Length: 198
Image 1 (cartoon, rainbow, N blue to C red):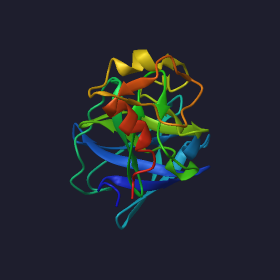
Image 2 (cartoon, one colour):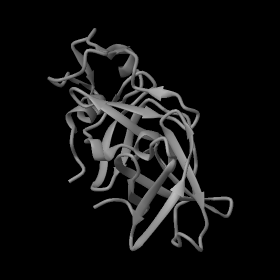
Image 3 (cartoon, one colour):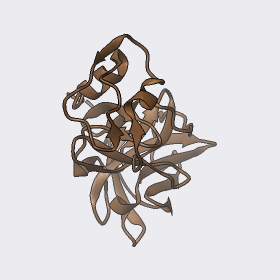
C-alpha cells in the first residue's frame, strides 16, 4: 500500500508522483523524462485526475496547483540534502527501503517507479530517475544533481552505519568498491533488504 500522497503520472512516459503542501500552494513532484518535452502531464491520485505543467531542473520536475484543484491534507514539503543512510522510495505500490548516498544509491525499482519521491525522515531529497543492474538507483535532487553515478569504498560507506561487523551481501554493484570483508549490520541489512515494498 502506497503513501497517501503518492500518485500515478502520465506524460511522454508512465511514472510516479507525489503531492505536497508549500506556502498555500499544492506541489506535485515527478521525473522530467516521465513528463516529456511538451512539459505537460496528467496526475492520478485518489479520485482526482489533473493535467499539470512542470518546471524542470535536470530530471527533477515540479508542478504547482491549488487546494481547489487538488484538495487533500497533503504533507508539508521539506527539501533536504542527501544524508548517507536509508531512504524510502515512495512508489505507487508501497515504500521501497534503499541505500542513499551522493555517490551510490541502491533500491529495487521498475520503470513505472520513475518519479517516486525519495525521502529521508519528513524531507524529500530527490525523485527517482532510473535504475541499473543489481539494484542500482539514480536519484535527482531539486537542484538537478544526479546522485548514484560515482563510486565509494565499502569502508568509507561503513563509517555512516551502526551495528556490529557483518558479512557483505552477495550481489553488490561494481561502483561499491569491496575493500573490507565485513560491514556494520545496518549497512548489510539495508542491502539485504532489497525489494521490500510488499
